[PDB]
Length: 202
Ligand SMILES: [Mg+2]
Image 1 (tube, rainbow, N blue to C red):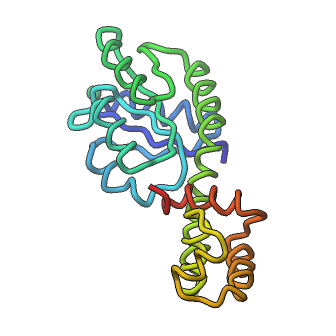
Image 2: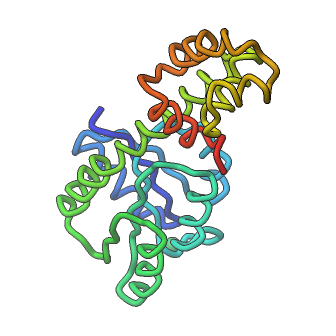
């Protein structure tokens, strides 16, 4: 499939149009006629592009952009607006929507817009996937390796790590080697970067 689209709109006419033009274009589709049906589903939705009514009851463009950011979703979001509501869509753009379409619109404008939005959002998809794995790599260290790693990324030398965590200075190099291989880090430098993505530096 060419991408999956989650459509949110209380107008059955719109849901039916979009389901048609998107299927006839090769995308998968899930329709939500109800705001909390979409929210209830969001934490186990796989990656896809959201196409939402800018004035969905309960979940307008601003409201949706805030809940998507709060749930830290990398799903790109397109906003469907009527001409009178474009000021509202603009506020959704300032909160990170990818684009908006004012109604009526041509189908190929929307499909083009969807392809582009999916292409632009896949780096942050892959990024959050990598942050997931990094967290798993951290979780897998032994408590002594977690100690050495905390030290290294805090900037401590071999001896300061050794007297802070009370470890023979002759074995730091060894827990460091184990940390590096389990973190798949090629240098202190990269180990600290991995730590930052993991949120162990704040
Ligand atoms: Mg509506």
